[PDB]
Length: 46
Length: 44
Image 1 (cartoon, rainbow over the protein chains, first blue to last red):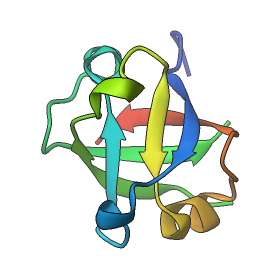
Image 2: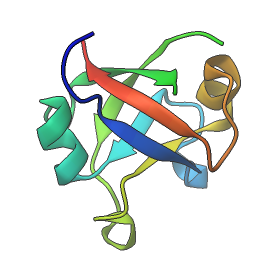
Image 3: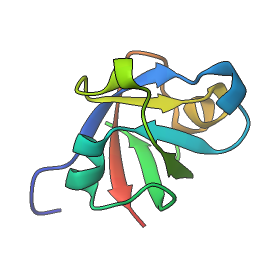
């Protein structure tokens, strides 16, 4: 696929977020991915 | 591994600027990653 992929390091979820299919991403990754809080993303291994 | 879909939530302040994504044990197992591995994140 063309262009630079957005790659991030996996860290464990905070306990209260576990089991909610949520991924915490900061504003810098959100800008590059092109998403806002509440949007959905695909996550896959590098 | 496989591709998963998750809802985006804000990062905690201490995680900001470290290129970190917080993913729970369920998504990690499905994706085929462990803590410290890298993932690609894409808008859907």
